[PDB]
Amino acid sequence: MKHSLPDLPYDYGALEPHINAQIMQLHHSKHHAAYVNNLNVTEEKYQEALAKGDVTAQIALQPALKFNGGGHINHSIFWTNLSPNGGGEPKGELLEAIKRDFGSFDKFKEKLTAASVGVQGSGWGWLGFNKERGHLQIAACPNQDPLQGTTGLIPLLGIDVWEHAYYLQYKNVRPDYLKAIWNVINWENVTERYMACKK
Amino acid sequence: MKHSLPDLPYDYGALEPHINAQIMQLHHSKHHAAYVNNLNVTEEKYQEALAKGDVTAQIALQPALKFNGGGHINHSIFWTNLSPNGGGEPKGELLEAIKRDFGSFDKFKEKLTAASVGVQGSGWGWLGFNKERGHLQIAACPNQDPLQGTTGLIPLLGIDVWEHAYYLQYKNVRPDYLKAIWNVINWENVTERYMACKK
Amino acid sequence: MKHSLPDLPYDYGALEPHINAQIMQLHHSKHHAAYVNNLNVTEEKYQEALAKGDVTAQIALQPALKFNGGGHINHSIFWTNLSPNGGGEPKGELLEAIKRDFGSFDKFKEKLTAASVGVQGSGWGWLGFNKERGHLQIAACPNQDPLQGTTGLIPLLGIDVWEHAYYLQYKNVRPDYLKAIWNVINWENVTERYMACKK
Amino acid sequence: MKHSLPDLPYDYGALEPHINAQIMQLHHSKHHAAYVNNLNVTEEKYQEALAKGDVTAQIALQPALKFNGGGHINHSIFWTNLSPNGGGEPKGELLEAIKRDFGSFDKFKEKLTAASVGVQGSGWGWLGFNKERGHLQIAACPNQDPLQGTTGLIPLLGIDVWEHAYYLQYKNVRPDYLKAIWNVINWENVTERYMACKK
Ligand SMILES: [Mn+2]
Ligand SMILES: [Mn+2]
Ligand SMILES: [Mn+2]
Ligand SMILES: [Mn+2]
């Protein structure tokens, strides 16, 4: 298919002072760019392996496909989850769901914060939608393992907790990065993803 | 190119009393057949996903491809590793390599036996060839994960220690199964795989 | 406090024709006994390592502790989940919860059956209780990994799908074993575990 | 036992300009300090669980013990592997082993460099000693999984490739950090670790 690096929907500095411009420029133009490129490389090798029926070659490529393929997915969603006009709380049916499933908005933040802080190593924190049960669910994933591909849950809000997402600004203090990132969350997109899961 | 269940090179009862016909008949005609057929199904689903660039669908299918693809691979080699004319010890350059890398033939047996008994759950014990280092190496693998695809080693001799491989005859006592199987090892084939990697 | 193999609450043949006596006799007196004894051995080695602060020795032993410790746990619950007076459906608050969380009793069976058949390799299928969310949840676990220790869910009903649990009687056809086992499920005990978590 | 943060054997800035002082101060006083403290917390909970025979509690703590316990080990070794007087190449029996097992010193650097660059996520690159085979071996480990505890190999040289080890200075360009770190390698310690493995 030939995957492409999506244009960022805002200037690299639109999220200051919560997430500085230096990070956004590295995260999009270097890190995300690397996942896409290698993903394109990986898929071409796999197409060859399928045509030859080289099952060994297919399995050796799996780690690279899940890693870079996941990277493309997770960051492509992540950018839309942030916005200079973001922050505050959601409204409408999403807020009603957060109240029902978690009790309140502040308790949801605490649990998703804890999931993101609890990730041991590199990974992501996620708010997702469980189609089968029809309710919200928090989950964490290691490295770039994607939410939907590995768990079946539909991503609504993702928090990147790889050190490159915050270290330059917040150093080892991951909890400050989590507290600041709530200021730029684009609940308008999260709502769309939530409403999309329902008929 | 569709994958097919290979014919067994000997009668189902050619390995009695070491491995009874009921095991060999179920192991080949029931267990192996299902991995192959399902692999063909998975490869069709995967090819569809690759053509659309659906990275989510590709990642969700990986387990079924590694499991059944590995199952097809592992059993296809396993059958060639056994023969009614087998047993005894190898000769030639293979025996010289086993002496050099493991000390003696009896020490290699202890090491591969120990690795195979050590599998916690289902898996396989393997003697393999490390191309980069140019020597023999034993490894164990879980479920139907294939050796070469996950480790880079070239499979020479595989021991299936899934319970369906022996339970009917030896029940829970895997060490009795391991003791019996050495009498039907096709050292003529193991040598062929070994000499092929060297040049 | 040393761990001990619990006595089976019924004769080895009390579950015929659903689970023959030969399976029950091997499963309890051979398989379960080994996990317990080895667990006692592992705990002694681990206690020695902890007292010396040998973190290396502690980490190297973790697999043996999770495997045999889980094996002891899982089987000790499994035996209580079966009874010759079992079968049929549950009643009371447990049945109401199954209807609310899964739709109906027949839908819960399909979901737990599907989860148990889906185990690739050895493992267990579980119905569990999520304390935080306060509802039922199905999960599968590999090898002898215990439910509560790895997921936080309280085990209510476990289905052992290790091949030694059924192969002698049903051979490779796990769906026949799953079909038969529902007739001996001790819904009286499953309820007791459920009501204990609620207050 | 009560583990303690070892004093660093040199000033935070003794490795400039290869590894700046800001990193060394964060890496030792914040990151390494966190692993120790939580490790002490984890071991106390485990001592309680062993005395009560709470096997569930033991397994729930395993991730925390391997993570922080490994962190203490890996960094405690890492500091001794660097030195302001470091760099260059080793001599004596270690260099002879590197020539025999890898071909040359430059080829060893390429392979250990590649292993360190290849780590997907957080982890470590290692040169180790295989006691059984009596030769050197390169391996990578994810997160803080320790070499000896998980593979049996004796650590000789470890390369920390967690992003916090280099990002502030080298940003996303991990390969530059690897090229620079060769300038401060304390081969005097690596030799001691190597000679210790031999009688
Ligand atoms: Mn990222
Ligand atoms: Mn098999
Ligand atoms: Mn069992
Ligand atoms: Mn570190």
Image: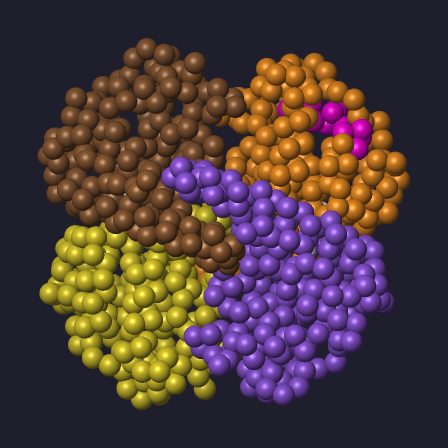
Chain colours: A orange, B yellow, C brown, D purple
Query: Number of labelled discs?
Result: 0
Residue D58 visible here: yes
Image location of residue D132, percent across then percent down: 43, 75
Q: Residue furthest top?
A: C92
Quarter of the figure with the C terminus of chain A: top right
Residue positioned 60% across, 52% down in the render: D3
Please tell me which residue lies in front, B52 or D129.
D129
Q: Is residue B104 above or below residue A190?
A: below
The answer to whether residue A120 is magenta is: no
Segment colored magenta: A180-194
Image location of residue D173, percent across then percent down: 77, 60
Residue positioned 67% across, 64% down in the render: D78
Q: Considering the whole magenta stretch, tell me its main secondary structure.
A: helix
Q: In this view, does C107 lie above or below A150?
A: above
User: Residue B5 appears in which quarter of the rendering?
Assistant: bottom left
Image location of residue B90, percent across then percent down: 27, 82
Q: In this view, does D181 lie above or below D119?
A: below
The answer to whether residue A192 is magenta is: yes
User: Residue C144 appears in which quarter of the rendering?
Assistant: top left
Q: Is residue B81 above or below residue D96?
A: above
Please tell me which residue lies in front, B53 or B114.
B114
Image location of residue A83, percent across then percent down: 81, 31
- Left or right, residue D162 beside residue B69: right
Residue A146 visible here: no
Residue positioned 58% across, 42% down in the render: D41
Residue positioned 74% across, 55% down in the render: D27
Please tell me which residue lies in front, C147 or D175.
C147
